[PDB]
Length: 352
Image (cartoon, rainbow, N blue to C red; front, side, top):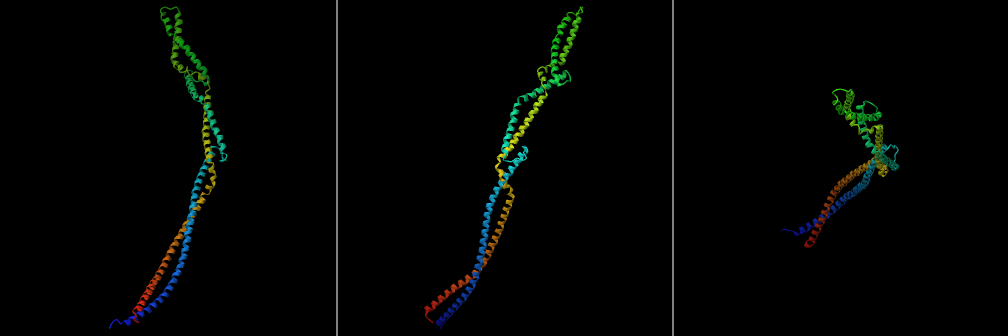
C-alpha cells in the first residue's frame, strides 16, 4: 500500500503554486534591484563624461606643447646667431674705432679698409730693396766707423769720411817708404867702412823707414779691414733709422688693416642675423611660457588620472550591483523552467 499517486498529484500541484508565488516574489526583487542598477548606470555616464573631458584636454595640451616646443627650439637657434652677430659688431667697433657702427654701412667701411690694407702693402713693398741693404749699410758703417776710432781715436761720425780717406793715404805712402829698409841697408852696409858724411843721409832715411815699417805693423791690419768699406762713411746714418722707422709704421698699418677689414667682413656675412633681435629679446620669456604650458599639461594628466580612478571605482560598485541582479535572473529563469516542466508532467500522467 505505497506510492499513493493521488498524494503525488496534489503535492505536485502544491509545488506549482509555490513556484508561481516565488516567481511573483522574484519579480518585485528584480524591479527593486533594477532601480539600483539604473541609478548607478547614470552615475557611470557622469564619470564617463568627466573622463572624456579630461582625456581630450590632455590631448589638446600635448599638441599645443608639441608645436610650441618645436618652434621654441628654432627661436633658440636664431637667438644664438643673433648674439654672435652682436659680438662681431662689437669687435669691429673696437678694432675699427667706430662706436656708432651699424650693419647697413659696414659694406662701405669694408672697402674703405680694404684699400687701407693694400696701400700698407704696396707702399711697404716699394720700401723693400732699400730696407734689407740698409741693415747691411748700417752694419758696415759701424764696422768702419769703429775701425777709424781704433786708429784715429774719438771723433764725430760726420768727420769719419774725410779722416778715413786720409788714413788710407798715409798707409799707402807709409808702405812705399817702409819697403826701402833693405835697399837702404844695402847702401849702408856697402858704405859702412869709412865715411863720406853720406852715411848721415842714409842712416837717417833708414830710420825714417824703420819707423814706417813699425807703422805698417801697428795699423796695417785695421787699414786692410777698412779699405773695402770706406764709401759707406759718406752716408748719413740717421736715414737708415728714418727708413726703418717708416718700415715699422707701414707694417703696423697692414697688421691693423688686415684685422680691421677682417672684422668688418664678419659683420657683412652676418648681416641677415641682425634681424633676429626679436628671437633673442623674447627667448627667456617664451621659455617661461613653454614651462608653464608643460606645467599645465602635468596638471591635466593628474586630473585625467583622478578621473580614470573614479570611473573605475564606481564601475566596480556598478558591477557588484549587477552581480545580484544577474543572480535573480538566473533563478527566475530556472524556476520558470521548473514550473513549466512539472506543469506538463501533471498533464501527461492524468491523475488529478
